[PDB]
Image 1: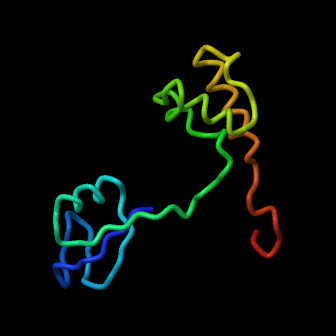
Image 2 (image 1 turned 180 degrees about the vertical axis):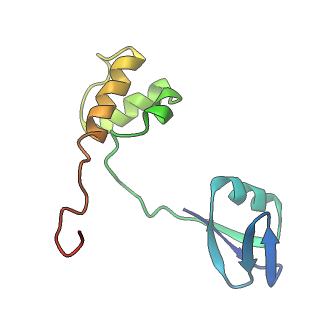
Length: 111
């Protein structure tokens, strides 16, 4: 997660985002580096998602995902992606786990 807080200003409108001095607001990577150039803000990025289940992603993202990326993914799963050499193999196998994420709130009082 990226966040910026106005240190130079008091109330400033960046593109379509409204920042105020003292007010931290979460921004995308685009705006983070955009405001990295613009010395009006203090920039801070922290990872709330330290570890998730790293073996299930968008096939669209995996279509543009590099060789070592696919490998490190399935390595975190605990499988050897060295046998799977073609993109088809690697993408399909990862898609099996995006299929394994069927439910999150299977708990009552939240249905």
